[PDB]
Amino acid sequence: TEASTYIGTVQDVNGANIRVVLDINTISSLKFVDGQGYRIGQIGSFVRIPIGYINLFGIVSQVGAGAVPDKLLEVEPYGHRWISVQLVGEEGI
Amino acid sequence: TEASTYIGTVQDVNGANIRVVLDINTISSLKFVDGQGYRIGQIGSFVRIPIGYINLFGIVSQVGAGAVPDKLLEVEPYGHRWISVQLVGEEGI
Amino acid sequence: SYYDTTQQLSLLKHVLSEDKRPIAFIIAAGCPVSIRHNDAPLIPDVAGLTRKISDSFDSLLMKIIQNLKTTIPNPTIEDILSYIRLLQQIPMSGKIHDVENSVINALEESICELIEEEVNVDLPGNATPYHKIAAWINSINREHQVEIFTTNYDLLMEQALEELNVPYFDGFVGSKRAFFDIRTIEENKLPSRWSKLWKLHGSINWQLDKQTQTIWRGTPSKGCSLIHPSHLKYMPYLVMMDQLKLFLNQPSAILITCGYSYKDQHINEVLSQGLQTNPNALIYGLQYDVLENYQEAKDMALKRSNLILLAKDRAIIGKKEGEWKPLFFKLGDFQHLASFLEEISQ
Amino acid sequence: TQQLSLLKHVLSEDKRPIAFIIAAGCPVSIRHNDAPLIPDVAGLTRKISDSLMKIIQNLKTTIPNPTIEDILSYIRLLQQIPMSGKIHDVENSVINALEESICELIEEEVNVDLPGNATPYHKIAAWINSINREHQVEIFTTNYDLLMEQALEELNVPYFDGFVGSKRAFFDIRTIEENKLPSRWSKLWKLHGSINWQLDKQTQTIWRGTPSKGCSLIHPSHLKYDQSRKMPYLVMMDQLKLFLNQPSAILITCGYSYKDQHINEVLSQGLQTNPNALIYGLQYDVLENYQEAKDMALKRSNLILLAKDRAIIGKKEGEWKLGDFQHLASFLEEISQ
Amino acid sequence: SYYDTTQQLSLLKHVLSEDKRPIAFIIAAGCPVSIRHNDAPLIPDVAGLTRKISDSFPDSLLMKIIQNLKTTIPNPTIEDILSYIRLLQQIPMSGKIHDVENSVINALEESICELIEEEVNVDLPGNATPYHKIAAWINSINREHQVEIFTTNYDLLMEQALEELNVPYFDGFVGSKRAFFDIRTIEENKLPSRWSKLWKLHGSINWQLDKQTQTIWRGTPSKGCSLIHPSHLKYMPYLVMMDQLKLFLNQPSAILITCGYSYKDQHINEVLSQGLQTNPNALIYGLQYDVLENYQEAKDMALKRSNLILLAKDRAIIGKKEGEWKPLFFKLGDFQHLASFLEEISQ
Amino acid sequence: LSQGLQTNPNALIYGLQYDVLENYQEAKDMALKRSNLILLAKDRAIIGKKEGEWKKLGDFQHLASFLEEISQ
């Protein structure tokens, strides 16, 4: 199904402030890819968002209850699986 | 299940300002471990966060309504069970 | 390698001042010896009873002592009583001592009569330490009531707790015969105000009525008692030890032993099992003697981490033996512990 | 026929926790070469006596006609005392040699293989297989033969007897209390012990494996409860008690002589405590031969007794039927179809 | 081009300290050699068994079988000779090849089996054995997914180590006296989470076939009667254990560590290949104790499969890229060092 | 088939025999072992692991005719 190097899906856009929901079932620790150990979304790490043929890159800026949207906290105050990603650049053809 | 010397889970990361939610069921009554009695999270006390193999230490900074995130207060302004840890160092191999 | 008394007492005072944690006690034979009524002690310790039996009773007694000493060290009253009952188990057991039997059955009755008449000593005035403990019991309306376990055959706890009328329940229900109940022990559906007192080694007012093979408590008869340490009847002992074990499994449970010599075997094993099962359990072992005289306590302390053993000169905490910082720690004495409890009460 | 058809629907009903007790009455019901495969308790005593009788008659002075349990316990209590030989002869050697000789003769007499597919045990195992109820049907055994679980294995029936492992299988204890077992898996408990259990000199282990040469655990009653909860007797007794305390509705016994006080007391306590429980203990003899059973029936209303001559129902004596093991197995097989 | 050991060891430490991820093991014939009871090793490897059979068993007639096997393949092992003997016994009048006839090969196979079973049936030494360390490590963390252990050995050393520390486990057989093999409970897979599993891919010495009823059972180790077979051709538990291994490799985020394995086997290598290819989330740590040049099949598999990690004593192949250690190194390949590492990370 | 019959008691098998009942010793043994299996032959009819007796379907053309009659 979902290929390796999978983290989540975009659920909110505010121009240059993306919010991502982690779709990993559990064990947010050492998702092995290509025999090398990378960690699930962390403050200093990058992410990649492929759009058809070009890949948008971004950097995580906030993790936890801060990245949760406005009224999602109102609906439930105990759910925190969001990250806030800020776009940086893109890779062309 | 949850072993001794357990306080709570990290619920927010802002680089070097962690926020922790206390899981103790209002049992801040001089928790005992290894023949000695420590106190549940206090202003000047240290906490330990283990990441797989290495342990991340830290020092509590503020306890109470200050540590609650920005809008969790707006949702429930009566629940104060958060502490604000600031990371200091770590132990190597 | 060094410990300070003040920090240990401060920690204990902090512990006792929490109502969330259930609290219990162990009142062994070392507490009654700590109060003097006449020039002689009010109730002698086990060595005192052994000496009194030896000098009060002869040839067959010495033969029994030699037989038991052939493979055992210095005996106790429990040892000789168990030996006598084991002999009574075998019908034609009179040839072991060449006494043709039917004489041991009267010797044991004589010993029981002597012990039951000696232990009935009555309590002195309202200044007794047990009165202070009873006053401390009902001082605070704790949400988890304090249970008490006693290995003493006497009734000092009863007199002290009734002189300051407090809620009480020992398992027997009734007014005329006080028939022993088992169900009401097991559902544990009682109001929190009622206190619980349990005698592991049996009292002196307990009478075995035989006939239907039923047990009942009440007025102490002459000669007929149930002083048995454990006995091997085909029982209060097993269910009551199960109750103690169940208590030790409660989360954040504190148990304090005063005047206990740790020389018993089943008690030590059940305590070790309870300590190992729930790591949050905590036992305060309080002694009044040199630490070198308790080998079993040393082994338990070196084995179980959450057991705190405190002696007059040395103290072992967290599998690490040490010495007090300049005998100290007079809290081992029953009088000092009672004064501590009554001063922390207010 | 009225009494039989009542329990047929109850057994056919689902959500029914079942249990069986197989005493010495069942092994006698199987005859090989015109003789029972396992001799009864009286037969065992006669065989032992055929191969020290002063102590036996001394016990006879204070007790009625004894059984091998009395002699074994008497020898054990003689061994407990340092020098108790003065009661009968001495030499501190007779008690030992007698004990291991009795153990060896019992061991050689009991370890007999099961005959062909006509054994009722096979029918019982087939019925056990034929039911896939949500609650497993536990089996209680007071015998020393390996017949029961040998028959279970011969029909590919899973069971758990408290021992897990290999040639030196230990006695796992905790997994009894979590009770997390497969639903299709059954439970087998041997109250009186087996002939393959063997204790360990270093520590109290009671591991089950290949039958040791002469060493076996028969009638475990002399251990001073050393290393509490390691004795298989107490844990099996607690398992029976907890099963009885469960709000079940069926319990069937067969071949029980009601000659044991320890089982009778716990049975009475459980029946008094549990009103919804039912007991269908049978009797392959005259109703008047079991005074203790009659007293229990008078005292306890929930117990239902059946005998060849009459039957007691609801503490009320009645008037004129599968006490024999073969008839019970045939009826169960017919009910399965 | 260069791989440094510290990061790999840290990654292994991070992996082994997690409880949610299912774990496994493969303990091949290379592990028992790494412990010495006498001056000689406690149990020899396959090469030692071949040497013992060759020098202990006219001699030309006996070596004719080895010559016939060598005519088609390189220097054979005990498995090849046993398979050839069983194939010969399959054909009734097959003795004309060597003019030996009945009981000349039939009794020779019995003698070989008796020799092997008496040589391998040995008791474990004291409580310092690495098997004891692994058994202690298993009890360290209260895992939610219990650790399974796959073995390619014949002995009962792991069983002794597991029972000595009171570790519940279920090897497939259930029962007390006869211990009939069960097939429903293996595939329904409703077992306690605490219970471990110990699958034997090549059988042990306590496995006996009673014929008659034609049912497999486990019990006391008899004299002569054994089921040493690598694969056999009987009219089968072997396929069941292989299916269990393949099913485990299909679990999400599965990790499998191999210690003492030589990769010379063909069925196991192919099964691992399909297991790795089918589920991209799996992982296989290949820990060897030799120079890397001795494992061509493992090298090819590592060059073909990306998520397979091969760590030799001098080189390493991680992510299809061969490299070299940056200062032999990586002593973790030996079973003693692996056990010491496990007991260190346990506490 | 024996393993399936033992595992599945609810299922039934209607094995036939276009011969005398005595020519199939293995079938007789299987019928005696497993009750779910039903064995019918020209000689008699084994029902419920028990031998019975008569007082046509063996022919395969007759079987097809019976199937057609049932369908029609």
Image (cartoon, coloured by chain):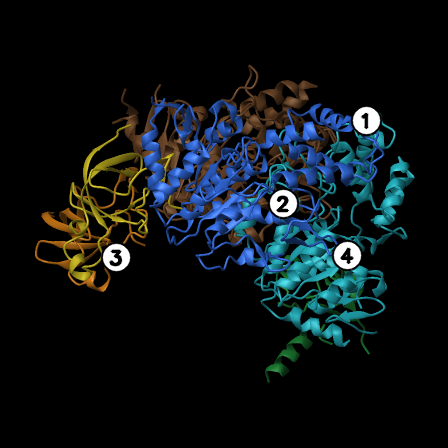
Chain colours: A orange, B yellow, C blue, D cyan, E brown, F green
Label 4: which secondary element = loop
Amino acid bearing label 2: Ile
Asked if marks 3 and 2 fall on the same chain, the answer is: no
Give percent across and percent down for residue E232: 60, 39
Looking at the rendered image, the disc whose residue lies closer to the viewer, 4 or 2, is 2
Asked if marks 4 and 1 fall on the same chain, the answer is: yes
Mark 1 and mark 3 in contact (Cβ < 8 Å)? Answer: no
Q: Confirm whether residue F52 shows in the render.
A: yes
Give percent across and percent down for residue B14: 15, 45
Amino acid bearing label 3: Tyr
**Tag of residue C204:** 2
Mark 3 and mark 4 in contact (Cβ < 8 Å)? Answer: no
Ranked by sequence position, the earlier of labels 4 and 1 is: 1
Amino acid bearing label 4: Tyr
Amino acid bearing label 1: Asn
Q: What residue is pinned by disc 3?
A: A78
Mark 2 and mark 4 in contact (Cβ < 8 Å)? Answer: no
Looking at the rendered image, the disc whose residue lies closer to the viewer, 3 or 2, is 2
Give percent across and percent down for residue E255: 39, 40
Q: Confirm whether residue C251 shows in the render.
A: no
Q: What residue is pinned by disc 1?
A: D92
Label 2: which secondary element = loop
- Tell me how far mark 4 sits from mark 3, CA to CA: 61 Å
Q: Residues within 10 Å of mark 4 (few under 14, many from 20)?
A: some
- Read off the chain for label 4: D
* Relative depth, front residue between D93 and E24: D93
